[PDB]
Length: 266
Ligand SMILES: COc1cc(Nc2c(C#N)cnc3cc(OCCCN4CCN(C)CC4)c(OC)cc23)c(Cl)cc1Cl
Image (cartoon, rainbow, N blue to C red):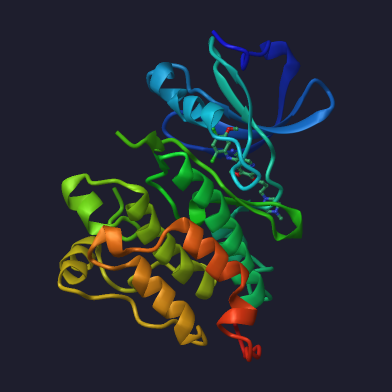
């Protein structure tokens, strides 16, 4: 065991946030001072080793725009402990009561933050492999953080968010994350709508390999849809870096859309 271990007794669960087929997620407190999120093991439901690989990844990654690992407890019951993101997933946020008030300036900034965290992922030679709005967490002041590193891996599957070469041939790279980032941009510009509306998984894969790409979202400026389409280039190496994405989105309203006016929804 390493320096991430803590004593269970210093963890107290309070408020339930969700369950799955491996355990649960609770709000809670740490050493009676610090608000945390705790992720639990339904003890015999899965191999605790592989249940903690999500923490092994989080130990190595540390960035302001990635959700921070706080501690692990490697003896049953088992926990992972992280900072607490007050507004939950970005997906829920966008669909929620606030989502409708968000306009393009806020959505591009959020996407800029996510790109910033992924740019870090990029230069660390990792791939996330599950980038999408459901796996971005939100705090106050519209802070967005990449989360859920379950499938994340040092570089050595829902087709809607996954690049083709990765879904078909298992070729996951930082460039298939770039693809997913392009899909995530349509989640932001639609306030959370599922991609490829009205298409089932098979139709998505068939159409995407046939060159089909989602059209420009209502009120989304074409320059932002260009960006999406660059993220969705057939050739992975011709997709932009997270470094380009971050800088492009940070400067967006001066360098690309200086004449932007708000409309009905964006
Ligand atoms: C601990 O370990 C892990 C925890 C997580 N997941 C979370 C992390 C992290 N990280 C941080 N913060 C979280 C906050 C949540 O909900 C906040 C309250 C919801 N409300 C919506 C309605 N409004 C009005 C009140 C707020 C939440 O809900 C499910 C999950 C969280 C992941 Cl993904 C992986 C690991 Cl290993």
